[PDB]
Image: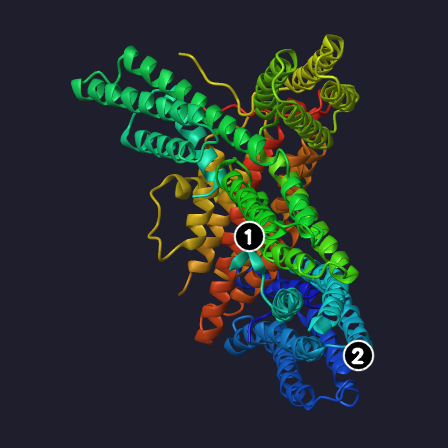
Amino acid sequence: MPVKFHTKTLESVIDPVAQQVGQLVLFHEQAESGLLKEDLTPLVQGVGIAVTNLVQVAASMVETSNDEDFKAELPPSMQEVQQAAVFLSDAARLLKADQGSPEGKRKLLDGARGVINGMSDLLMCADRSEVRKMVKVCRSVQEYLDVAKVIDVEADLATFLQNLTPGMTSMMKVVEQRHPELTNLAHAQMLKSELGTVREQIPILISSIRVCCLVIVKDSGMKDAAFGRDYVIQKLFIAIEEIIRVLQLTTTFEEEASAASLAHMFHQAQDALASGDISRSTLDAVRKCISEGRRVAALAATDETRAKLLAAADELDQILKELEELQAKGLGDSRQARALAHAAAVKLQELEQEIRKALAERVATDFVNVGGPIKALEDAALASPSDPNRQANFAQKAKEFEAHTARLADTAELVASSGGCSDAVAAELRKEAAKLRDISTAVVPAARVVLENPGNQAAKDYLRTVKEKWLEAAESMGRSVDGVIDSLEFMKVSEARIQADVKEAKRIALAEEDSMKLIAKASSVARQANRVIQVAKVEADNSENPEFVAKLSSASESLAKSISPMVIEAKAVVTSPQNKDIQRKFCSSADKVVEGVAAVRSVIEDNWVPPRPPLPELLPAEMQEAEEMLRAPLPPKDQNPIHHAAASVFREADQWDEKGNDLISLVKQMARKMAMMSKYTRGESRSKADLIRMAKEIALNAQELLKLARQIANACMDKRAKTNLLQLLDRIPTISTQLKILATVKATSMGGGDARADADATDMLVGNAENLMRTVKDVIRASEAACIRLRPDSPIASILWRKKG
């Protein structure tokens, strides 16, 4: 039974006691080295009193509960932890008598680990009781959900409703009581999200049941209404399943390529090419970037960007062949090899930019009219029964809707896979896409119930509700997509497409072709312009720069004030297609639209900043030993996992020079300290005090890192990168607290005793430390990303992000 800290009460109780026990070990080693004999009696009395009082408040509950599992599991843990406290008392006695007392050392370490693990179990049987109760409630309501499938009259829906509401409330009050107690923010977020799902799905369920009760008397569309109802029942069932699963998690989540790794590989290949490097590694990375370029080319919106991306790919391959022929001749060091490699770096940047342009083009095409097709489907379902072709229209609009939403989700997947977004934004985008598909499965059945039940108002209202759910999911997914996509590229592509479509509309307006072409092209222009408005809104929201937000607001508002007059002038042309004056009015209005789009593009263009840094054109004995370790060859992977993680961090921070950058200094120092910790846990033959003290030093270093990186996030005017850094900073403190606790547990188990306890203690310590190192590394990269758009006055602006050498 490992130590637990998934609960604020668990951490709150175990943290100070583990600190006191660690101090007992530190004092024992302070007298072992002969520095000063310290009497451990007061500290042991404190730990023993904490144990006694926890045993008191826990023993007062053996009568109060009404589940026999808790009453059965309490006494063994109580006697266990009390026995460990006794071991601490004996340790104080014997070690006070003789420093070299073997029984004193043994009982000191044994009782030391036993009060920590024992307190953990003492609180954990209670926590298991609570979780069993909550899961019991969730199981009851989840089981009662299935009764809704037999409801056919609104009386059954009334009784079922009045039985479902109190149970649902009893579940939500308990879960809403639970998630403020968890130490893992991710678990709390999952609980809150599923709570939202249930709360929004209840009235949908009762509504779908209502349409079933109305359509059962048709003596017609029963299969699709039943499909809708059972779809909502399954969504509720799954959400409650996930609530039950997260309720029972007692583990840290973050201890259980991508788009950001593709972008990082692009940038690493660009930096290595801009230098002198043309080794096999760099060329392999370049070839991977070419493969990504061709992969995006196969999914391009038009054959022009496809053939262009392929052209850049084959050009880069040719440059690679030329570089390899140069290197084969012996001219790898020559200036023409370096100049050719630098040209390859520039071409790799241009390939990256064209990839961004292709994604922005896919977004410009697929999201130009998100709500159109589903509105056409709803109107197709609402066709009067006299319409001799309502079935064909409904079928066509249905298939067009399915292909539309499928295209939206596919484009979201492409952006998530190649948009250079962080892993968190990518996971969120993919989640919103999967939700969009899932809710899309229910759109056609509802509209088909309306189609075959005209005089049914309940089916109409349910179809409208499902329509608004689809529009909500699709619009939020669109907001995420616009958040990832490079906005300047969206404004350029939209400016060009709007120019071509406005030109074609003026052509159709002057030379009298079909007015249907004119209203179609004109409304398409209006939709593209409004999409420019929306993307400008997302870009303005993401900036904390008030002047840029004001300018962009002026451009977007000025553009929006020109869209409607253009459309009404177009309709005026369809009224009098022969009037040349109305044609002139419409042409001037459309030109005004083009000018507004150009204005928004100009604001975003003038606020544009190069993302990454540009290209070129040509100690104490402890930290010193850790430096020699981290610059020596790596230890065998099986033997020093902590050292490997610390080496990945040290290597991530080592490519940057330290002057003018305290973050790199803190991170390098933290890597050295973590390597020392690895060495101290590896000791088996003291290393305990060095392990505990080293853990505390790493914790303090993590505190300072959180302070500085928070100062960097505060002065950042890019809410995307700001959020990216804060998401990583928010889990560091719990990691460091768990680090100190787990290192204190490991120190009291290594060097004799139990083997299982030492194994689990080791594995938990190394998992925690690996997670901490991953977090610190991602904090390096996220901080470098946050230092791109800093306020011109903050001191953080003076930070130096120049590559070493």
Query: Which quadrant of the view contains residue 744?
Result: bottom right
Kind of residue sitting beneath label 1 = Met
> Mark 2 near mark 1, Cβ–Cβ under 8 Å?
no
Residue at 46%, 28% in the rendered image: 302
Quarter of the image containing the C terminus?
top left
| Mark 2–mark 1 distance (CA, rounded to whole Å) | 57 Å
Q: Secondary structure at mark 1?
A: helix
Q: What residue do we see at 34% from left, 13% from top?
A: 339
Q: Pointer 2: what residue?
A: 163
Quarter containing the N terminus: bottom right
Figure check: 113 above or below 796: below
Q: Which residue is mark 1?
A: 694
Q: Is residue 332 left or right of residue 731?
A: left
Residue 619 point in image, percent of width and height: 51, 36
Q: Amino acid at mark 2?
A: Asn
Residue 640 falls in which quadrant of the image?
bottom left
Q: Is residue 341 left or right of residue 608?
A: left
Q: Is residue 665 visible?
A: no
Q: Quadrant of residue 248?
A: bottom right
Q: Is residue 507 visible?
A: yes
In this view, 153 is above or below 552: below
* Label 1 environment density (alpha carbons within 10 Å; few <14, some 14–19, many ≥20): many
The residue nearer to you, when weighing 333 against 84, is 333
Across and down, in percent, residue 82 comes to: 66, 82
Q: Is residue 683 left or right of residue 403?
A: left
User: Considering depth in this image, is 532 or 369 the residue closer to the camera?
Assistant: 369
Q: In the image, is 749 to the left or to the right of 243?
A: left
> Which of the two labelled residues, at mark 2 and mark 1, occupies the earlier sequence position?
2
Q: How is the image coloured?
A: rainbow
x and y, in percent, of residue 265 in the image: 42, 34
Q: Nearer the viewer, residue 336 or 677?
A: 336
Q: Secondary structure at mark 2?
A: helix
